[PDB]
Image: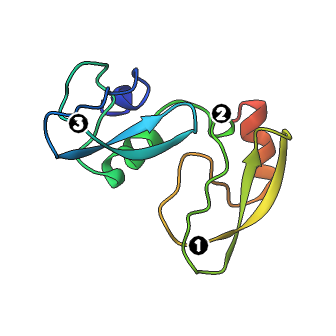
């Protein structure tokens, strides 16, 4: 149940080693890379960003509880994301770069999952 690590307190960074790891930052609602080797904190850390993303995709946490993330690529794939700041579903240009749980195929899906569709 690696999705547990996703929903655990963030792993604390470390200035001992130069090695880096992935961790789900609840303040931004996305997986981020940071330097450190398990120098205290929670179990919220992963081998890489893909492992983090997949773990947080398997997490029960509603997609509407995460912020908009359509990647930072240069693709042009229309997809729907929930805006947590304006509390509304909008279409964004998917860049093709990973993402997070907040990722919908349709406006209906977005709204219904905010209602609590599961």
- The extreme left residue here reads 17
Disc with the residue nearer the chain's start (2 vs 3) = 3
Q: Find the distance from the CA under tag 2 to the CA under tag 3.
A: 27 Å
Please name the residue that numbered disc 2 is placed on.
65
Q: Residue at x 28, y 51 (%)?
A: 48
Where on the picture, by quarter, is residue 107?
bottom right
- Element type where label 2 sits in the image: helix
Q: Residues within 10 Å of mark 3 (few under 14, many from 20)?
A: many
Mark 1 lies on a secondary structure that is loop
When the figure is inspected, residue 32 is found, relative to residue 11, above or below; the finding is below
Task: Tell me the mark number nearer the camera, choosing from 1 and 2.
Answer: 1
Pointer 3 with pointer 1, Cβ within 8 A: no
Residue position marked by numbered label 3 in the rendering: 36
In percent of width and height, residue 47 lies at 22, 46
Neighbor class of circle 2 (other Cα within 10 Å; few <14, some 14-19, many 20+) is: some
- Mark 1 or 2, nearer chain start: 2
Q: Nearer the viewer, mark 3 or mark 1?
A: 3
Element under disc 3:
loop
> Mark 1: few, some, or many residues within 10 Å (few <14, many ≥20)?
some
Relative to residue 27, is residue 107 drawn left or right?
right
Between the C-alphas of marks 1 and 2, the distance is 21 Å
Residue at image x 56%, y 39%?
Answer: 29
Image position of 29 (left or right of 104): left
Q: Does residue 44 sit above or below 78 in this rendering? A: above
- 40 on left or right of 16: right
Residue 55, percent from left and from top: 38, 41
- Pointer 1 residue: 95
State the image coordinates of residue 72 (x, y, percent, origin top left).
56, 67
Which quadrant holds the N terminus? top left
């Amino acid at each position: 149940e690696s999705w547990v690590s996703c929903l655990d307190p963030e792993q604390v960074t470390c200035e001992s080693q130069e090695g880096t790891h992935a961790s789900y930052n609840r303040k931004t609602g996305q997986c981020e890379e940071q330097k450190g080797t398990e120098c205290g904190g929670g179990e919220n850390h992963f081998e890489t960003l893909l492992k983090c993303n997949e773990s947080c995709n398997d997490a029960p946490k509603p997609p509407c509880s995460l912020e908009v993330d359509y990647g930072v690529g240069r693709a042009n794939i229309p997809r729907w994301y929930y805006d947590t700041n304006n509390a509304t579903c909008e279409m964004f240009t998917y860049g093709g770069i990973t993402g997070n749980k907040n990722n919908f195929e349709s406006e209906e899906e977005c709204k219904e999952t905010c209602k609590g569709f599961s």
